[PDB]
Amino acid sequence: NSVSVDLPGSMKVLVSKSSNADGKYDLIATVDALELSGTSDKNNGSGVLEGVKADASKVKLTISDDLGQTTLEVFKSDGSTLVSKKVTSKDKVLGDVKFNEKGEVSEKIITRADGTRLEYTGIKSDGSGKAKEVLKGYVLEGTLTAEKTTLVVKEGTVTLSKNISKSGAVSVELNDTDSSAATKKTAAWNSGTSTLTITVNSKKTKDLVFTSSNTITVQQYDSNGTSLEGSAVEITKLDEIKNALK
Image 1 (cartoon, rainbow, N blue to C red):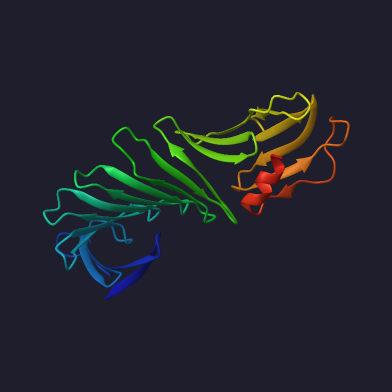
Image 2: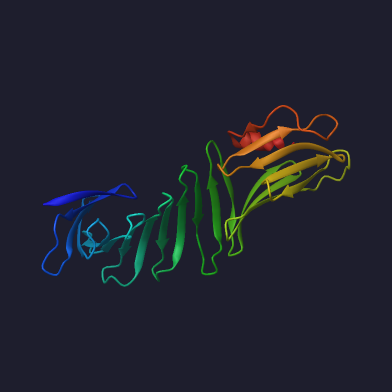
């Protein structure tokens, strides 16, 4: 009969127990009440399945050879133009992409393995658009260009900018329009530790760490401005980032 195989993207495929005269395996999947079917030259669940939506949209599910990746695509009725593409990679990261009527990317939502998200919307032909980072407890808003995502938090005369390069590298900067050397914040970015050190009046005041866990922590310096004190506190809401910039 058939063997149920577990797939990335919360899907399952049934694969025939044995091959056919061409040596090929039959594949069957149900994706949100839509029946897909296909044939594969592998025996493990990998290969291509196809179906048709009630509105005649073509649907294709492609399972990579090692079962690490799935790609669920919807096309126009002639199968020529993409409508949407959902890719779950072997690190369980999800890419959810919408296309315009010309088959060009117009929206991309990336869901990280921890559930945080990058939301790119209104994407134009130059790769520019609106950007949103959805974190645990708060959201960061900004813009996308082909060079970088820039997310901005403003508090008083201070503007904090989180940059994510097109290659995924994070840098952070801080700009203050405050004129008084007594109150004005400046900041230095340490790329090796993903840490922004803020200074007021030639004394370090706090370290903002932008962690690999997609959180932000804040830790104060002692009143001298030289050593850290206490321990870093994880930001849980947008108000607490704002407080760090006061």
